[PDB]
Image: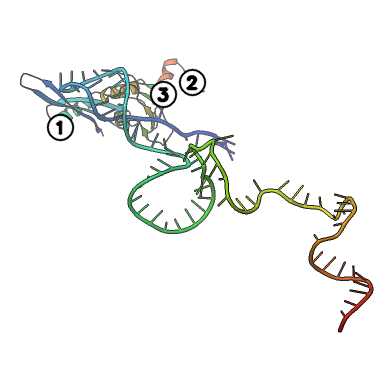
Amino acid sequence: ELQEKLIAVNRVSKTVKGGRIFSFTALTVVGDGNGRVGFGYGKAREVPAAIQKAMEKARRNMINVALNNGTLQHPVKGVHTGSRVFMQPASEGTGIIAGGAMRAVLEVAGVHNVLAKAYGSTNPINVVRATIDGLENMNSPEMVAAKRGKSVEEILG
RNA sequence: AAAUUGAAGAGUUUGAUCAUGGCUCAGAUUGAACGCUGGCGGCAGGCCUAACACAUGCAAGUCGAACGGUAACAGGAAGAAG
């Protein structure tokens, strides 16, 4: 159904011979609510054009991650530039406890219950990339049963 | 059976960026103090400072079934005044 979220709107400037020229960047996320997450980074001279750029960039580059009934599979460490995200699956209930950008990514991802923490720089673009890296780093019991070459019950016990 | 189901960030260095890195904020608490305000009840608490100096009153007595006794009080026995 492709629900959409706007995370950050930044104003950046490029200096020229006349003076400063200001443009606006938008960081967005889209998601199915079931597994599929995508993030977009648009840049335009005025704001809603940058929002529309970020949305049509985010809708293309979406990756699907695996997740249980509303939860993760294991603890997983996502990393990026200055961001050292750590997300732990949850018990049921308790909502998404996560800060800001990571909260928006996990909410469009369909992750209902999570315990998350950001380390290092909490810059929004880099923590969105660290979050989605930790999400696509995650692996399922059926795929780790496909790897090690045995049924899932012999792994879980 | 149960004995715990646990983890949020933001602002500020720049023309703008990303890092590093301080500073500050959002919470909970207290033997609290002060300012404005003030209906009641329950249960707790109340010199953190001068281990400074203390007026006044009380805070350790009991036992006659240990004893000599007998000041009180209470009767007794007697002698009396009526």
Q: How would you rate the neighbour count of disc 3 (Cα within 10 Å): few for under 14, some for 14-19, many for 20 or more?
A: some
**Mark 2 → mark 1, Cα distance in angstroms:** 50 Å
Q: CA distance from mark 3 to mark 1?
A: 37 Å
Counting from the top left corner in percent of width and height, residue A118 is at 34, 25
Image coordinates for residue B52, horizontal then vertical, percent = 53, 38
Give the residue at x 48% y 21%: A155
Q: Which residue is mark 2?
A: A155
Chain of the residue where label 1 is placed in the rendered structure:
A
Q: Nearer the viewer, residue B67 or A149?
A: B67
Q: In front of the other: label 2 or label 1?
A: 1
Q: Secondary structure at mark 2?
A: helix
Q: At numbered mark 3, what does the secondary structure look like: helix, strand or loop?
A: loop
**Residue type beneath disc 3:** Pro
Image height of A155 relative to A94, above or below: above
Write down the residue under mark 1. A48
Q: Earlier in the sequence, mark 3 or mark 2?
A: 3
Q: Chain of mark 3?
A: A
Amino acid carrying label 2: it is Ile
Q: Quadrant of residue A11?
A: top left
Residue A57 x, y percent position in the rendering: 20, 25
Q: Which mark is residue A75?
A: 3
Same chain for the residues under marks 2 and 1 in the image: yes
Asked if the residue under mark 1 is in contact with the one under mark 2, i.e. CB atoms within 8 Å, the reply is no
Q: Give the x, y percent position of residue B3.
A: 54, 34
Residue A41 occupies quadrant: top left
**Element class at badge 1:** helix
